[PDB]
Image (tube, rainbow, N blue to C red):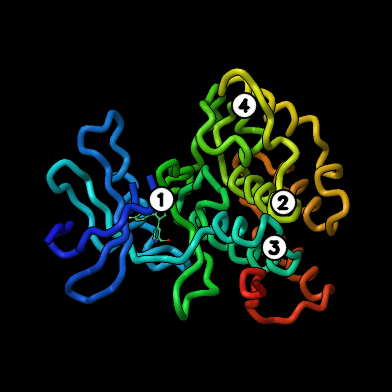
Amino acid sequence: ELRVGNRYRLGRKIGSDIYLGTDIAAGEEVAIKLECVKTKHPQLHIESKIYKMMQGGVGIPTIRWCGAEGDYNVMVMELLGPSLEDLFNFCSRKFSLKTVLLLADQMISRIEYIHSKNFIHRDVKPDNFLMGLGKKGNLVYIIDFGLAKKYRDARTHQHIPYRENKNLTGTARYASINTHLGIEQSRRDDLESLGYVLMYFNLGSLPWQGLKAATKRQKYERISEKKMSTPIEVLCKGYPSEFATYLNFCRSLRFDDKPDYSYLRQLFRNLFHRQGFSYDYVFDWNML
Ligand SMILES: OCc1cc(-c2c[nH]nc2-c2ccc(F)cc2)ccn1
């Protein structure tokens, strides 16, 4: 009887807001996102528009419903599996090289797809990639367009202008050095963030993680400084050279440069082949 859109039965809250739901018409399991209508800065209706523009892309979740009902703005999405962060903790924060490469291949393509649809994600983090369910269990999905920005005109492909003095929009742990410097984010920053996520998977933690400071402000300065002070060769020591090559390539991109996604994917595909890993989708979580 407690429904949203007069169709989706409201279930347990799973994230602080995201709930489990059930489509009463189909019997299908869904995820429900609620935004208090009285919030200071409304984001859900804007985010729904981004999801809608992304529909049809590989690993883009389907948006089933959106609207305002009582005290909330509502968005209903198809139910997906756990996030890569949930899976990483489930695997005791250690992923094998094979799993990192299988993930890298799909994550680069998800980012490329968002960029082909004229947006930058701006919050590339393990928490924002989810595995599918059932038959789509080997498919990596990208979520959360709350911080996404249009970087180019849909018609002309004119890139947004270079701008400085920007607030940190994203997670400090994975932010590109340009983001720390307050430079307007662009295609390169989503890819650089992905490079840190892959190194976080390789290492189990990042060298600028767990830094202590009196305030959030001083904490972000310490993360920024530590990230600046750590050469890519030091960060990637003891891991295949492809991870350093990937990161140097992303840091070398100019503000409005179109990244070579095919080259970056091929670096990791060539390493997968050289390693002699089996061509299956047996991730580390399937070995537990
Ligand atoms: O793992 C179950 C699961 C979680 C999520 C999820 C995790 N963070 N945010 C969402 C979400 C949910 C509904 C929505 F409309 C938009 C975003 C989505 C789908 N399936």
How far is the residue under mark 2 from the one under mark 4? 21 Å
What kind of residue is marked 4?
Answer: Tyr
Name the quadrant of the C terminus.
bottom right
Identify the residue position indicated by label 2 in the image.
204
Query: Which mark is first along the chain, 2 or 1?
Result: 1
Mark toward the viewer: 1 or 2 = 2
The residue to which callout 3 is attached is: 100
Disc 2, ligand 1: is the CB inside 8 Å? no
Foreground label between 3 and 1: 3
Q: Is residue 67 above or below residue 40?
A: below
Judge left or right: residue 33 versus residue 281.
left
Residue visible at 61% across and 38% down in the picture = 175
Query: CA gap, disc 3 to disc 1?
Result: 33 Å
* Residue pointed to by mark 1: 154
* Residue carrying label 4: 220
- The amino acid at mark 1 is Ala
Q: Earlier in the sequence, mark 3 or mark 4?
A: 3
Q: Residue at x 65, y 77 (%)?
A: 282
Confirm or deny contact between disc 2 and disc 3 (CB under 8 A).
no
The reply to whether callout 4 and callout 1 are in contact (CB within 8 Å) is no
Q: CA distance from mark 4 to mark 1?
A: 34 Å
Q: Residue 84: image x %, image y %?
A: 57, 58
Other-residue count near label 2 (Cα within 10 Å), few / some / many at <14 / 14–19 / ≥20: some
- How crowded is the residue under tag 3: few (<14 C-alpha within 10 Å), some, or many (20+)? many
- Snapshot quadrant of residue 44: top left
| Amino acid at the residue labelled 3 | Val
With 109 as the anchor, is 32 left or right in this view? left
* Residue closer to the observer: 210 or 134: 210
Give the camera-side residue of 56 and 256.
56
